[PDB]
Length: 7
Length: 7
Length: 240
Length: 240
Image (tube, chains in turn cyan, orange, green, purple):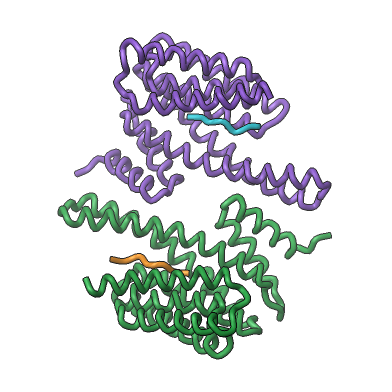
């Protein structure tokens, strides 16, 4: 799994 | 009023 | 090895998936300009239409937003903003003119001469009407009139073929009626005609649906719901 | 009459509203390059960040889609598609490198030297970390390592200032922690550190919220929910 949340 | 729907 | 055309088509679908529609357009123009006496496949013609639709659609969206803001700053006499807002609008309008000129040249140089069936002729003449219509949307006076004349001539040519050669439930014929009606309404400011044409196309489709069915129900269904939506909007706005 | 800078700022907000982010970037670069010893306002610095974020974000999105497709055609040994898909990816990666190089040059030539408070220093060093991170996302081997080193150095410099000069509930400090954690997770493939850093930043913010409150609750609240979302995702994936 990849693609987290970033600011 | 304007902006209908078009194909 | 793949042909250049096979390669370009595949690139265009990659561009579509990445939402890079300007590049999609260029891949499909390489395909179109590589034609001989043959014409585009249904898939290719739809890739080219989708690419152009997206490219022009972003600009039309931006144009509408900028026009709202301009009208609002007009209503306050705030003139230094109005000038900058119009500088911006002029830029967007230059892109709209370039984009339309691309597909319009392509239409009469390659696509329309190549069309060999009723389906593709109507498809390309309606596209010609559509693109002239998008020019009419932001021009005034003499330039506007010319775009309007061009739009009407194209749509009329498309409809003569469509009504005699395609079924009333055909998505392209229905799409032509929808757009033609919108042309009367938004460019000619003639809601009377807009409604009659939309209503007639809707009614003929219903009649054919009720007696013979139609092969591609999904597409026709969506367009006929669009025709209804416009009729409901336009006729409620009339009695207002 | 309006100053050129006033004019450029207004144009940038028009560009934002029309969603023409490349042009937004150019307006805000004219502002930034016109600075003397003064620095950008909070509004200007945020317009510049928003413009760049949007410009790079469309390419990162396209890159991700194209990378999925490439991996899928890899799994079938379908090599002529793979080559075309990689041709396409290379194009997107060239734009990503250009975009990052624009803001990275601007950061060390104008923005970072101009920063006069803790807020703006952390803001610009985190931006420097972010942009190096976006390079790291698609590079490998030696080029990747360099981007990773650059990212880590920038984030570390930002965090030294942030932890000593901003409140734990400050949106910029929290944003830095979120991104820094994501860097450990997605570039360094180190979920252990990623969680510890995210958890520590979340916990210090909670502690400050529970005793002193915070002025800008809205922003902090959203970022701390993002920190939680990542912790929940990362720690559920661990026990898998």
